[PDB]
Image: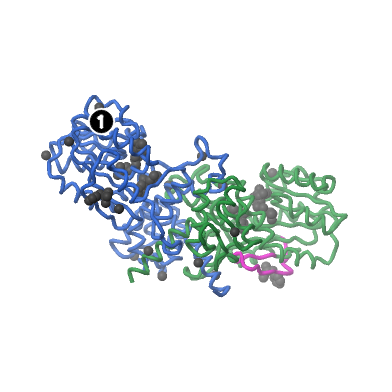
Chain colours: A blue, B green
């Protein structure tokens, strides 16, 4: 390449950083929904309506425009050639930046081994939760509902491992009005958020929550309710069960603690293999590099496939997700 | 086409991690190792610097995802954009390690209701580490060209926003007799600069004082200002703004430094009309960053238009290559 080509490529990498951050912010502030409905927007009007500092609002749209996501026309912003694609994956940009940005920013301090004890990185939990709701819905739901449609029975008590916001249990209780639900989450803040949200939607008597580590599910006290659970779900946290030996034992413990579970629906993103560096798709690099930074194991799809029998489960159906890196839903029994 | 859009959006995502990795790779030693040898071994690098190797691999994968380096097994090689990205490594460091929190917290920083008190956070030590190389890499040519055209030998020099003290030191090395005086608003700045200066043996020659250069009249160091025959102010001048404040600050500086012959003022400025898809490195970060921080940023013609009211005359102006649109003015 020429020096001019390198110059353009490096300027684009710099601007991409600002656009990337802006995709999450623009989602969250309501701009991308406006642009997807009407195809355009007036930046002063948008700034007044949402009581935002207009000079910053101009930067945000400029940052998006600098890489072809939107176009600026006088007072107006219109959707650019990459709008649909960036909008589709906006929760992933949110996750990377608003949720995870401080991890990546602190690369020089996170990488040194002597630094890597106790609290050594900081995520924004609320922001991660904010993004995870759309990540679940947008990428996981169709496979999730296809698995639910093919259960071959009607659930009476469902337990969700890593229940977070409580939304999955709420949706299951809408599909199956008899159903009792039980969410396990390790984070007491998620427990508080979930109990609150469930109560406001009218489900406080049907759905309840317990703080607990699903890696040590054999220690969770939930008034003997686990024995009545006949459906188990776990989405977007199963990599936490790994390394392999930890995972085998966690699966057996799940198997013994939920002895009346018929189907166990397990959904997660996985570590890819042999994608060429210049062909990496959205998410993949951030998912893998981030967990490598945090010290968290990420299995491949073949590692999952290979653990289940030893774990006490049989995989009877598998669904490919489009495309949140390489992600899947397993139907286990 | 849907495929192009997919590739482009993936590139934007990956560029975020590469961007952050440039600064990190600088800081950690990897960029200089690649400069020397053109290549390096990942395991070796990790072991030498005692780094968690899975993360080190992701760092390089990040740089590789967009062409800065190329991976060949366990080896990393300089890539097509290595020279350009290394050249600008301090601007990535500034964008990410320095100012990343500001940009991450965009959703919280834009609402007016939240814009009171300390409503954004910068990493001051990181900013200072990037600004030190920014000074030397982008402003040195024009700064020294201005020094060469002074037409006198300075006896006492003052530097506003002296930071690390490096400018004073370098002046001292070029004009052995000279005395230096630095003024910085932050005690962090005063501390390092004072240590640095002693370590280098310039302790009698160069001293410092905490002070706000916007209100230079209330700086009770006073004594030596009258001696100063050269004033310098680099990468903070936009702090004097908005306009009316800048007029006052310039007049105050004129009157607090009456024997100053030349005043060398260098800074980056707000550009005008650059089309969005042709924005060069830094511009957008600098401008959008100052807009989120609520700080005024003048264009070059605002600066041109303020010196006379401010009590100075611009005798020579130097364009900079290219830190957005940057400039050094020679005022008297
Ligand atoms: N070992 C563990 N045991 C229980 N909960 C866990 C856990 N590790 C992570 N979590 C929880 O798992 C959640 C992952 S965020 C995704 C949540 C949810 N399954 C959904 O699809 O929306 C967080 O709430 C976190 O607190
Ligand atoms: N109003 C003000 N008065 C004095 N110093 C200021 C200031 N606003 C910012 N600064 C200082 O300006 C410096 C900016 S960065 C370092 C610039 C230095 N002139 C150089 O070329 O290397 C910081 O040390 C900061 O404390
Ligand atoms: C929730 C998140 C994750 O692993 C993390 O934030 O550590 C995640 C998991 C799976 C797909 C997308 C994001
Ligand atoms: C010091 C920095 C700046 O204004 C900031 O960090 O807010 C700066 C000024 C001018 C050129 C580059 C960086
Ligand atoms: O081994 C697999 O591919 C999956 O883990 C589950 C599966 C196995 C056999 C038939 C269907 C699904
Ligand atoms: O107005 C300008 O362009 C500069 O601020 C200073 C200058 C003016 C005239 C001749 C040289 C320099
Ligand atoms: Ca409009
Ligand atoms: Ca365009
Ligand atoms: Ca840092
Ligand atoms: Ca920390
Ligand atoms: Ca029912
Ligand atoms: Ca129980
Ligand atoms: Ca059974
Ligand atoms: Ca792609
Ligand atoms: Ca397989
Ligand atoms: Ca080698
Ligand atoms: Ca390449
Ligand atoms: Ca935020
Ligand atoms: Ca003062
Ligand atoms: Ca360019
Ligand atoms: Fe994770
Ligand atoms: Fe500034």
Q: In front here: A130 or B312? A: A130
- Confirm if mark 1 falls within 8 A of ligand 12: yes
**In the rendered view, does A222 fall on the left or right side of A123?**
left
| Residue underneath mark 1 | A257
Q: Nearer the viewer, residue B9 or B202?
A: B9
Q: Read off the magenta span.
A: B311-328
Q: Is residue A289 visible?
A: yes
Q: Position of residue A227 (x, y in %)?
A: 20, 29
Residue at (28%, 55%) from the top-left corner?
Answer: A321
- Mark 1 closeness class: few <14, some 14–19, many ≥20 residues within 10 Å: some
B264 or A267, which lies in front?
A: A267
Whether residue B321 appears in magenta in the rendering, the answer is: yes
Against A118, is A53 above or below?
below
Residue A176 belongs to the span the image colors magenta: no
* Residue B32 falls in image quadrant: bottom right
Quarter occupied by the C terminus of chain B: bottom right
* Quarter of the picture holding the N terminus of chain B: bottom left
Residue A196 in the image: x percent, y percent? 28, 34
Residue B18 at x, y = what percent? 50, 58
Taking the image as shown, residue A28 lies to the left or right of residue B263, namely left
Q: Residue at x 33, y 61 (%)?
A: A35
Q: Position of residue A8 (x, y in %)?
A: 52, 70
Q: Residue furthest front?
A: A310
How many badges with numbers are in the image?
1
Rendered view: B91 above or below A129: below
User: Can you name the residue that lies furthest to the right here?
Assistant: B177
Determine if residue B87 is in view. no
């Amino acid at each position: 390449v020429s020096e001019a080509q390198a110059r353009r490529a490096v300027a684009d990498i710099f601007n991409s950083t600002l656009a990337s951050s802006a995709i999450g912010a623009a989602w969250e502030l309501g701009a991308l929904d406006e642009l997807r409905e009407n195809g355009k927007l007036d930046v002063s009007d948008f700034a007044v309506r949402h009581d935002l500092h207009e000079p910053a609002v101009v930067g945000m749209f400029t940052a998006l425009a600098s890489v072809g996501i939107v176009r600026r026309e006088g007072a107006t912003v219109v959707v650019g050639p990459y709008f649909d694609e960036a909008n589709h994956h906006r929760s992933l940009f949110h996750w990377l930046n608003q949720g995870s940005g401080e991890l990546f920013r602190r690369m020089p301090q996170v990488l040194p081994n002597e630094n890597r004890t106790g609290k050594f990185y900081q995520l924004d939990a609320g922001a991660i939760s904010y993004a995870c709701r759309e990540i679940s819905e947008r990428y996981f739901d169709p496979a999730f509902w296809a698995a639910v449609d093919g259960l071959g029975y009607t659930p009476t008590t469902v337990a969700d491992l890593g229940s977070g916001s409580g939304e999955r249990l709420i949706q299951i209780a809408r599909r199956f009005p008899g159903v009792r639900g039980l969410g396990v989450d390790i984070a007491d803040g998620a427990i508080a958020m979930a109990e609150k949200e469930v109560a406001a939607k009218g489900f406080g008597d049907q759905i309840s929550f317990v703080r607990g580590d699903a890696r040590t599910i054999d220690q969770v006290s939930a008034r003997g309710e686990f024995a009545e659970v006949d459906l188990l779900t776990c989405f977007m946290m199963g990599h936490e069960f790994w390394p392999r030996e930890n995972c085998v034992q966690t699966l057996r413990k799940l198997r013994a603690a939920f002895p009346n579970v018929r189907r166990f629906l397990l959904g997660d993103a996985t570590r890819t293999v042999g994608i060429p560096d210049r062909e990496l798709p959205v998410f993949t690099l951030g998912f893998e590099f981030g967990h490598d930074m945090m010290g968290v194991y990420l299995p491949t799809l073949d590692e999952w496939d290979g653990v289940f029998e030893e774990g006490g489960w049989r995989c009877v159906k598998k669904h490919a997700i489009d495309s949140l890196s390489v992600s899947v839903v397993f139907e286990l029994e």
